[PDB]
Amino acid sequence: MKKVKSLFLLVLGNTEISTIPGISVAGATPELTKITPVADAEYLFYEKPLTIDTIPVTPEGHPTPAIITKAARELSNFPILVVRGGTYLAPLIPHVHISNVVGRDFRREPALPEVEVIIERAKLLGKELEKIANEIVIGESTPGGTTTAQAILWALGYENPQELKEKVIKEGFKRVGIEKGGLKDKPLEALKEFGDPMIATVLGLSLGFGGDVVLAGGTQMLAVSALLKSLGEDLSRFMIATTRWVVEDPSATFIETAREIGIISYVAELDFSKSKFKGLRDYERGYVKEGVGAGGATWLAVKAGYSPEDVSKKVEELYERLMGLR
Amino acid sequence: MKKVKSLFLLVLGNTEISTIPGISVAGATPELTKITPVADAEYLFYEKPLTIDTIPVTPEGHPTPAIITKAARELSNFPILVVRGGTYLAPLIPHVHISNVVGRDFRREPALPEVEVIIERAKLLGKELEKIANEIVIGESTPGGTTTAQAILWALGYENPQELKEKVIKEGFKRVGIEKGGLKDKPLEALKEFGDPMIATVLGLSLGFGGDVVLAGGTQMLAVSALLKSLGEDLSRFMIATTRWVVEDPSATFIETAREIGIISYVAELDFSKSKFKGLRDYERGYVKEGVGAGGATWLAVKAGYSPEDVSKKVEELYERLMGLR
């Protein structure tokens, strides 16, 4: 039974958590984090996004990693479907609709009281995609997603920007009445309490699609992996795909946590040192590191025969096409 | 480059035209035609639809032909994606979003002033699907769609329920200031003036997807075929797939028009004569005849090795599962 080798999915999400000042840099201000996921998605298909005509940037002016995804797709031609897990806005492109839900601020109330329907609709999507593709590579764009992901990891027992995050997570834990590890065998409750629509969508996709699944991102994808394990999912058909920058970070525990869950890791060896642009050159200095399935997209481009250097070259070329950056 | 053999798409649409009493029987009343396309789509994946829990029926109580589509999918397992071309409501399932536009009453104003963006987004969808599938089979559910389709056919020069339709079409023609054949080389204008979001979506899909396309329906698909031809599209990779009931109808000119456009025709040989249920038995008497890509779905089930008799058997079995019909 013939199927496409690999299909890349970009799952979009939002959470009220990204409104909290200092919590996310996926957009120039907390307000603009509301636009980031749609602009990222739209940019993949058009010379500039459509909802706004400039690509998302950090307050520091570092470009969205959507540029890496776009580059890798432009070299290798892999198929893509955008999936709206739950966001403030629909992106202005064809996309799969799962929900229009935004995750709540988990300090005040449960994050995701639509969790069951989101998982159910994503599960159903996974089940139809299993008829079309042997493998899905699931990327994401969800400002605030690393805080929801960390809350879930902590809740399941996996141990200055960081201090705000701990504070915010600790407030949510106090609301719910748990300590670290308190929900280690209650994965659905952890997700309902501290999740977001992207995590719920990736989880449902993973549960519904029966073939190989490459979870393309960082801490977000560790949280998904940990939920899967806690739900008893056999993890041999899952992999996580991230970047050099993520695994090299001495502040992060990516490999250690990945090995504690028991999921294998793919690591895209991108290097922007030779870039003419400080916004790209700055990826070598801890900034951005990951997002929009960039590591996963690069992995697909490499499987298609390109080098990480070739992808980096495409990125530098797309960046020089960019007009109207601040 | 491996791809799935065939992907079935169900394109959903609405038009204000289906509000006009007597114009459509795709639903129990003109108001309920607003719900028909979502209930049809939802029923394909669940034992009962979700927006309402009973399947759409004609005022006479003849079941939606979605039952045929569901049967054929249940036997052959073909992949399906639902596509919302433009409808009052989103269906409560994962689906591809093109627009939330409803076609206007073309007697009063142009049908589809969102025509360009609808075609553009559907075109883009077609282009990504060409990477995944060798062939698409495009069905539709759009109450009022045969009147918009006939308006377009007449406008492009292709010659009691019928008298209301002519009247309504003639009023739209008087508004625009044309006679039959008046837009034969102005296809986009015919679509903007007299179309609906499903016709625009199927057209964009057809223009964007480069492989074999099976247009699964009747008069609706003739209109799409005629627009394609008028746009200079090479029609060798297109086919239309309909049912016995459509081609046997002495009131219709399906084969003659199909041959005038120059598109070949597939004809699903379903026979419900042996059915225990008058609602199904009544398909032999001119009622319903086509919709929801039923002919196309049957064609896929036959290519997968099943007989038209096997599909008819599945239909009769799904009908006996149905609870709470009037």
Image (cartoon, coloured by chain):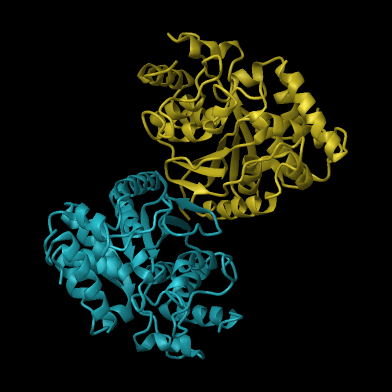
Chain colours: A yellow, B cyan
**Image check: A161 left or right of B86?**
right
Residue at position x 57%, y 35% in the image: A140
Question: Residue B42: where, in percent of width, then height?
Answer: 53, 64
Which image quarter holds the C terminus of chain B? bottom right
Question: Residue B114: where, in percent of width, then height?
Answer: 33, 49
Residue B124 position by quadrant:
top left
Q: Observer-nearest residue: A97 or B161?
A: B161
Residue B192 visible? yes
Residue at position x 70%, y 18% in the image: A161
Question: Residue A58: where, in percent of width, then height?
Answer: 55, 19
Residue at position x 17%, y 67% in the image: B154
**Image check: A12 left or right of B142?**
right
Above-or-below relation of B55 to B125: below
Residue B262 visible? no
Which image quarter holds the N terminus of chain B? top left
**Image check: A275 left or right of A213?**
left
Above-or-below relation of A197 to B85: above
Q: Observer-nearest residue: A296 or A65?
A: A65
